Image (cartoon, rainbow, N blue to C red; front, side, top):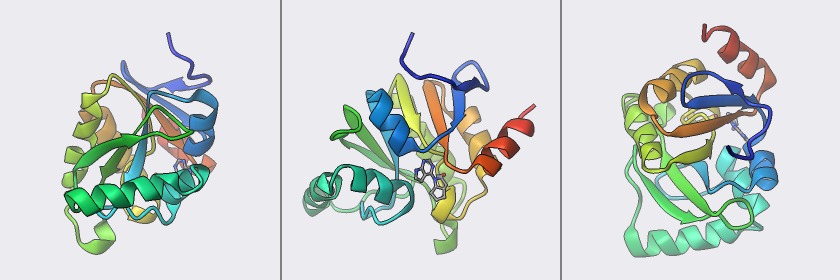
Length: 167
Ligand SMILES: OC[C@@H]1C[C@@H]2CCC[C@@H]2N1c1ncnc2[nH]ccc12
């Protein structure tokens, strides 16, 4: 039993809700919140910019130190950093950016990072400003993640479409 509320169950291990991941994180304070990061951990907009804003830029400060030490992430890769006032931890995951010419096959690799955590609050990777199809992304999530994932879908129209076409 966990403190997530109002989610639809999609499969044995995937749950979805029409919600802003930032608001879900503030309310639930989960163990792991996923960020839809880029390789530079430059949290400008979308999921990342909104999460970072909610941390009063502490996420960006921590991220800049991480990059100065370790260099950029790989597309498809991740790192675990603090969750600040939103969660215990933040799993920064880089999906491929199709508007950069990056291979959509790396989306499966991106979701594989979720399997290192028993329970996560997450967005749909590569959706939004990353340019990918959110229905394809939801299917990759369902077919890749085996741990318990609670998906927050920001756009109501998209949520309705994902749920109705899922079977
Ligand atoms: O797939 C990520 C979706 C696509 C949307 C268009 C751009 C970013 C948006 N995303 C969000 N998803 C969940 N919570 C969110 N809070 C703020 C943004 C946001």
